[PDB]
Image (tube, rainbow over all chains, first blue to last red; front, side, top):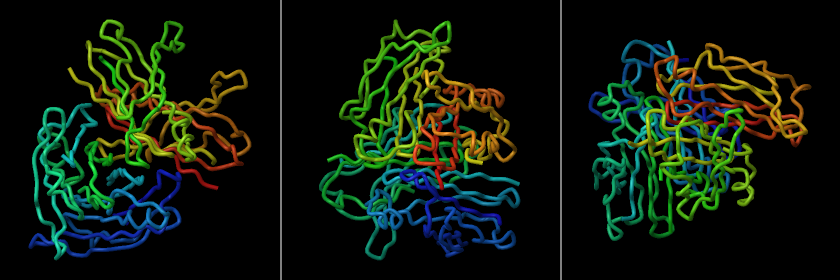
Length: 115
Length: 115
Length: 115
Length: 115
């Protein structure tokens, strides 16, 4: 499992559950092609988006639907989504854990990259 | 002006100076239409991006070129750039300060919205 | 003045107004000696805490009463307060802006140090 | 395991390994009494600090020695340490995961509290 995304709710101090996200990969013609998608579990984690073989070198974008998350909780947030755009595997295969920490008017994203 | 961006460097403890960014407005065909850009001053701030009359309701994107900033400092970054996407003015005109706090493998974006 | 504190509210997307804080300097017996305090203005800023002549080298602590802030908004917070502890002026006099970004179950503190 | 602390390095995008921390509990006479201590593992996690039985209601402080971490990597950071001060178990036993995200001039702390 070379790509994992974890999402936390900084208002409730809890995992952000059932958060939808879509992953895209930049194609040769410079457009965003749909790569993978899923929803966070009860632990706020989304595993199994891709495989070592499929997750080749490229520029990837993860668009996390934070607006729907907040709206469902009664909140009109600032951001439409939280985005992570990154070049992956440019020095060989790596494991990526993307952490998103959510507040109604602020988010942070962090990457932990391991061998 | 109704939009200001401030950028800070969490490695050096300083304003992030000469950081380039482009501002886009989502078009009817939902492509992104560029409409403003600039680079942060010596105080890490970018003002004068738009005016009250131009800054109408819509979905806006600020694309901050964080990668080039880290490149210039000789530090390996994770993200291609830092994309702040938000619906503007949804209630009516507001003043927006977008604050971006940068680290090589993490960033946060916060909005301060005043009326 | 050589020390300024700015506080932002990540739930409301606003300056955090009327946030109380105390500043301490570590004494010889390594107890904390209070020496300044105040509350954030309507811009979320607290200025005039000290002067260039008073702000000598040493270890300083800013104790931000985040709990009372969240209490006043009717929101359950995690932390008792947000303690910024730093060695000042270690090279010589600097100007410090401490920026605190607050959520109920998360906070970040960043220093902008200029010379 | 009712208390866990995880520490990440936002410069390298990696767990922050061998980071020392000390936990204190506020006594009846309002002083800080030593409660527990340890170092983060290769995963940047510190488990086993306490037990359900021992971890009674109280005000707890975790002081994470971030300065030694950065110094060992050649960096003179802003903060002396990262602190987490919180009331625990005031509504019955809870599980606490404290996440610290470290940069030389900035840190964030987040709590995930579960049943």
